Amino acid sequence: MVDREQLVQKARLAEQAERYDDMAAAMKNVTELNEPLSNEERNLLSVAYKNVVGARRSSWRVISSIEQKTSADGNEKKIEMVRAYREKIEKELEAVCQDVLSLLDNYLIKNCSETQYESKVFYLKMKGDYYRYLAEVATGEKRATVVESSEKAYSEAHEISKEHMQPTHPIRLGLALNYSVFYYEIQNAPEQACHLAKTAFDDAIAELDTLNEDSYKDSTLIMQLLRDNLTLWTS
Amino acid sequence: MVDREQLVQKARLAEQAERYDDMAAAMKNVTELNEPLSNEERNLLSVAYKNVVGARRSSWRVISSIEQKTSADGNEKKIEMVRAYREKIEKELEAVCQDVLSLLDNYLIKNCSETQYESKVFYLKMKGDYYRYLAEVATGEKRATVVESSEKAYSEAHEISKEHMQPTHPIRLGLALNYSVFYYEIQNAPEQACHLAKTAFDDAIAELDTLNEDSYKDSTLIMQLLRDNLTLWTS
Amino acid sequence: MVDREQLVQKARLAEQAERYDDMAAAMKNVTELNEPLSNEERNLLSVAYKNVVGARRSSWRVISSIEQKTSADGNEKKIEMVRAYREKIEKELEAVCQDVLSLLDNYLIKNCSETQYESKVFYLKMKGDYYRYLAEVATGEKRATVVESSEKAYSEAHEISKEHMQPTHPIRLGLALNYSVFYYEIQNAPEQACHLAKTAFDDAIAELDTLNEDSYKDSTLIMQLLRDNLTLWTS
Amino acid sequence: MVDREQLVQKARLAEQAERYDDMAAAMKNVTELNEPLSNEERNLLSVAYKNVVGARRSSWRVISSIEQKTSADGNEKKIEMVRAYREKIEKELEAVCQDVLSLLDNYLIKNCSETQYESKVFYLKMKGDYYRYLAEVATGEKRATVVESSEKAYSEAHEISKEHMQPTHPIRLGLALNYSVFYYEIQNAPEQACHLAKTAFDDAIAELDTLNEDSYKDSTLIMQLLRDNLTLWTS
C-alpha cells in the first residue's frame, strides 16, 4: 500500500534520474487513485509522457530514415530487419499514446467538473497532442481517423480557452503553439498554421496587462516560440 | 564631409564586423555633430563603448592575474614587463573611460532638455558605469574620488527614473542592475546591493501591467538578471 | 529463427536509435549462439553494456546524492521513498553487471582459445570493469569480495597484454586507463594509480614506432586520457 | 632599450590577453633585431599574424557579404559607405600581408642558412599563405600576380620538405594542408587539391613509424584536418 504523496515523490525522483518510464508509471498510478490531479500532479504527468513519447518519436524518425535509405540501396537482405525494427518502435509509440489517451478519456477529462476550465483545456490539449503523435506514424484510413480525433480535441480546447482564459495564459498560448504545429506538419495548411500562431501572439501582446506574477516567464517563453515558428514558416 | 546617416551606417557596419573601436569612433563623431541623439544612436554609442571598455577590462584582469602570480613566483627578472604591460592596458582602459565621460559631460548630459527624462537617466547610468570601470583599476585617493563620482551619477539617475519611469522600464531596471553591482563589487556592501536589486525586481512584478509591447522582452531579461545576481549574492 | 547477421544489424540499428537496452539484448543473443565473437561483435557488446550500466550508474549517483541530503534535512517522512528508489536502481545496476559477468564467465572467457590473446585481455578488462561497477555500490564484506574479483581480473589482463601486445595497442592502453581508475577511485591508492598510468603512457611513447595504421587514432586518444587523469590526480 | 627576452615575454602576455596586434608588433620587433628566430619565436610570430590577418579576413568577408546584398537591394544611397568600409578593411588586410611578406623577404628567408631546412620550409609556407590571403581579396591582373607568387612559395617549400623532412613532420603536413586549400579555393582545382591532400595523408600513414615523441599530437591533428578536407571536397 503506497501513498499518493510517495508516488508524486517517486515521479520527482525519477525525473531527477532521467528515468522517464518510471516517472510516467508513477503518475499513471496517481491518476488511477481515481481522484482529480493538482496543477503540480498534472504537469508531472505531462512532462513524464512527453519525455517517454519523445524518445519513441526520435527513435522512430531515426529508423524510418535508415529504412528509406536501405530500400533505395537495393540490398533486399537488410530491408527485413530495418522494417521489423521500425515496426517494433512504432508499436511502442502507439501503445504509449493509447496509454495516455485512456487516462484522459476514462479519468481526467471524464471526471473534471464543468467549472475546472483550466483542467479541461489542459487535458484536451494533451488529447490533441497524443492523437497528433499517432497521426505522424499512421498511414491511409488509420491516419485520417487519428487526424480528425486530434483536430476535434484541439478545437474543443480552443473554444474553452478563448472563453475562460486570458490570451497570455500559458495553457492558452501552449495550445495555440501545438494546434498551429498540427496545421503545419499534419494538415499541411501553412496559411491556417500561420494565422493561428499570429492571432495568439497578437492577442497576447494586446492584453500584455493580463500577465500574472506567477507565470509571466512561461507566457513570454511560449510567445517567443510562436514568433519563432511564424518566422520559420513564413520564410 | 561625411553625413550623420552615413556615420550611423558605419557604426552598424563596424558592429557586424565586430570592429568595436571603429564603431565607438563613428558614434563619437555623431555625438560631436553637437545635436541630441535618437534612442537608436544612444544604444549604438552605449554598445560600442561597452565592447571597447569590455575588451580592455578583460585584458587588464588577465595581465593583473599573471602579475600577482609572477610577484609570488619570486622571479624578479619577469615582474618588470608584466607590470609595464598591465600599466599599458590600464592607461588604455582609463583613456576609453575619460573619452566616454567627456562625451557625457560636454555634450549628452550638458545639452539634453529638463523634459527628456529617459535621455537624462540613460546618460547618468553610463556616467555611473564608466566611473565604476575607473574604480575597478584605481587605488588609494584616486579610487575614493572615482567611487564618489560613480555613486553621485547612479543616485541622480535613480531619483529621476523613480519619478518619471515605470518600474518595468528597461532603463530603470538596467540602472538598478548596475547600481546594485556597484554596491556589491565596488562598495563591498552586500546588504545594500541585495536590497536595491530586490526592491527593483519586486517593484517591477508589482506593476507587471506597465509592461510595454515594444520592450517587454528587455524588461523580463533584466528582471531575470536581477534575480540571478540576488541568488548569487544571497548564497 | 533469427540469423546472427540480423542480430548484429539489430544491435547497430538500436545504437543509432540510442536504445541501448535493445542493443545489449541483441548482443547478448549473439553471445548465446555459443560461438566466438568477431572484433566487431566484441566492441558492439562492450558499447551496449557500457551505455546500459552507465545510465544505471548515473541514476544511482543522482538518487544517492538526494538520499544523503534528505537524511541530513531531518524529514523522516521523505527518507523511505528515496532509499527504496535508490535500492531499486541499485538492484538494476547489479543485475546488469551479473548479466555481463555471466556472459564473460560462461561463454567469452570460457571458450576463447589460449592463442586468442587480444580476445582474452579484452574480456578480462570487461570483467575487471563490471566488478568495479559492483564495488562502487557495494558496502562491507560484499564490497571486499567484488574489489578482489576486480583486482584479479585486471591483473590477469595486465600480464597477458604485457606479454602479447605492443604498449601502444588500444586494448593494452584502455586496460591501463581503467585499472589505474580502479586504484584511484576504488582502492584509494593515488600513488599506484599514478604509477600505472605513467608507466603505460611512457611505454607507449617509448615504442611510438609500434603505432598501427588501423588504430593509431584510438592509441593517441587513450594516451591523452591517461595524461589527463595523471594531471588531475597529481594536482 | 628593450631586451629580446622581454619582447618575447610581451608577445606571450599579449597572446594571453588576446591583444594580437600587440603580439604581432612585439614579434615584428624581435625579427627586426636582425638575428635568426628560435622554433618558439617562429611559432609566436606565426600565431600573432594569423590572428591579426584572421580578424581582417573575417571582417572583409562580413562587409563584402553585406555589400553584395546592398547592391542587389537597389538602395544606391547605402552602397557608398558599404563599399568604402569594405575598401578600408581590405587596405588594412593587404598592409598586414605586406608587413609579414617584408619580414620574410628581408629577414627570415633572406638570412636563414642553406642548412636550416625546417626554418626555410616554415617561412616559404608563410609566404605562400600571405600571398593566398592577398589573392582572396584581389581581382584582375593584381590577382594573377599574387596567385603566381603564392604558388611559387608553396612549390619551393614542398620541394625542400619532400627532401629533408619525414612525411609525418607537422611542418610538411601543415604545408600540404594549406597548399591543397590554395588549389581548391584559389586555383579552383579540386582534383589537384584532393591529390595533394591524399598523397600527404597516405605518405604520413605509410611512414607512421617516423612519428616523434615531441610532435606526434600535432602530426595526428593535421592528418585528421587533411582527411576532413578530403571528405568535404570529395562529397
Image (cartoon, coloured by chain):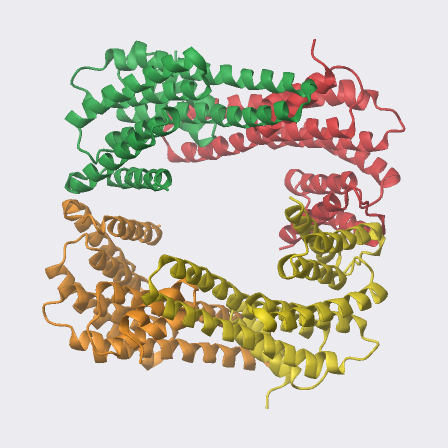
Chain colours: A orange, B green, C yellow, D red
Looking at the rendering, in which quadrant would you find the N terminus of chain D?
A: top right
Whether residue B62 sits left or right of residue A90 in the image: it is: right
Whether residue A166 sits left or right of residue B97 in the image: it is: left
Residue at the bottom extreme of this rendering? C1
Query: Does any portion of residue C215 appear in the rendered image?
Result: yes
Q: Quadrant of residue B13?
A: top left
What residue is rendered at 43% in x and 29% in y?
Answer: B15
Residue C220: x and y in percent read 73, 53
Q: Is residue D17 above or below residue A73?
A: above
- Please tell me which residue lies in front, D102 or A125: A125
Residue B58: x and y in percent read 49, 28
- Please tell me which residue lies in front, D59 or B175: B175
Whether residue A46 sits left or right of residue D53 in the image: it is: left
Looking at the rendering, in which quadrant would you find the C terminus of chain D?
A: bottom right
Q: Quadrant of residue D129?
A: top right
Query: Does any portion of residue A71 appear in the rendered image?
Result: no
Q: Is residue C21 above or below residue C201?
A: below
Residue at the right extreme of this rendering? D115
Residue D43: x and y in percent read 72, 31
Q: Is residue D194 above or below residue D130?
A: below
